[PDB]
Length: 134
Length: 43
Length: 29
Length: 221
Ligand SMILES: *[C@@H]1O[C@H](CO)[C@@H](O[C@@H]2O[C@H](CO)[C@@H](O)[C@H](O)[C@H]2NC(C)=O)[C@H](O)[C@H]1NC(C)=O
Ligand SMILES: *[C@@H]1O[C@H](CO)[C@@H](O[C@@H]2O[C@H](CO)[C@@H](O)[C@H](O)[C@H]2NC(C)=O)[C@H](O)[C@H]1NC(C)=O
Ligand SMILES: *[C@@H]1O[C@H](CO)[C@@H](O)[C@H](O)[C@H]1NC(C)=O
Ligand SMILES: *[C@@H]1O[C@H](CO)[C@@H](O)[C@H](O)[C@H]1NC(C)=O
Ligand SMILES: *[C@@H]1O[C@H](CO)[C@@H](O)[C@H](O)[C@H]1NC(C)=O
Ligand SMILES: *[C@@H]1O[C@H](CO)[C@@H](O)[C@H](O)[C@H]1NC(C)=O
Image 1 (cartoon, rainbow over the protein chains, first blue to last red):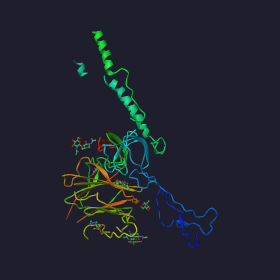
Image 2: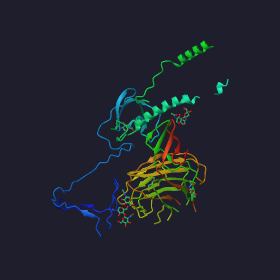
Image 3: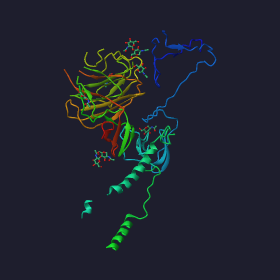
Image 4: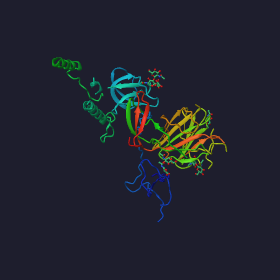
């Protein structure tokens, strides 16, 4: 709302058909004839409760392609042939780990059983296929 | 000597139905049942 | 497989059923 | 023109390994025994629809790559090749003689604000069937390929190959139109077919390679 002129912001008031999720529409064609955008008040005071709020939404993609935005937790050393609790790139589990001959195709990162439970994981920094045996 | 050339389906149905029953019980672990994941470690 | 299913062995082994089946044959003949 | 004889167009649907397993997936596959368009000529402009199967064969190499866009201008993915690298851009240009043939880049490809690049070594580079699959999704453009060796000149070879992934660039474009780029009386084979959200059953062998597929909706068997 600052008097330096920050109150340029505006919203689409009229639209032909509902906007899809994560879709965008920049058009300003005339909507009997009306401009399709309308600007908020946002003077040093708007109406009460109509102050400008800044917003950001974080969308977490979870595609199971190689992960690229990780939390600050540092890795441990890696144990084989003992049953161990583990967290690989966010895949929490529990089992006995073993460097495994059932080699993935080079693009693949997890293996799954008949059930969705994962039977193998590619270790994200030694790059070996661990068998997980429950 | 003719028994070598000759009902086993009525017995194999036991082996096949127990196999299919267990396999179906395992496959239902992949089912979400409305949850955001089929694997509890995800939740 | 690992998901809590387990198949238990029968009490009578296949060899024990063969022994009984042999005993029924031997007796019969 | 059209051609039909293919059990081709299967690809690995998941980034996850499966072995000695028959698995059922719904994904945008090429329906079995459909009609691919066939051309071997110009740089024609075509619909992308839900996705594309593409393949080529030629003497030496003459496919240079591809153009895509929300419109034939809007952010418009370019993928073109060096001798040793593919190089990739997201910008708008005023695609209007939109070819890379004679009138390592050109075609008024003046980028200003929109490059969002990629560049890498695995692509169509000197090796005969240059199989590709392209699949735009929300935030996604995962591209697939297989350089299947063949003896045929320009008729579509019957047989089975499964395409591996090659890259994904999160372009954010909603692509609607598509075109190829050749280089230059010359001629070379290429084929195009639109993907559909079919259900397939896939036969992963012990190696975890897809050895067979059955297009579930093809026929009653
Ligand atoms: C962003 O970059 C594109 C080019 O990638 C610019 O496109 C030009 O747009 C003007 C109209 O504004 C046209 O007359 C030109 O023909 C376009 N050039 C090309 C090569 O397509 C666009 O103007 C740029 N926008 C901003 C805000 O920088
Ligand atoms: C994965 O596929 C390859 C290729 O078919 C198999 O490798 C062959 O295995 C046999 C038996 O060990 C050898 O005689 C061949 O020489 C191997 N070929 C090559 C090119 O190395 C491999 O066995 C398969 N993996 C599994 C787990 O079955
Ligand atoms: C989809 O395409 C239309 C033009 O065909 C465009 O106006 C719209 O912004 C596009 N959507 C996205 C998310 O880019
Ligand atoms: C980075 O990854 C490599 C494997 O490519 C690994 O050997 C190395 O230890 C990792 N870096 C550090 C600092 O550990
Ligand atoms: C393919 O195209 C031909 C015409 O060239 C048409 O008759 C046919 O129905 C189409 N589909 C199939 C599956 O052949
Ligand atoms: C690859 O192509 C770009 C232009 O598309 C060019 O600038 C670059 O020098 C080429 N790379 C090589 C190794 O020739």
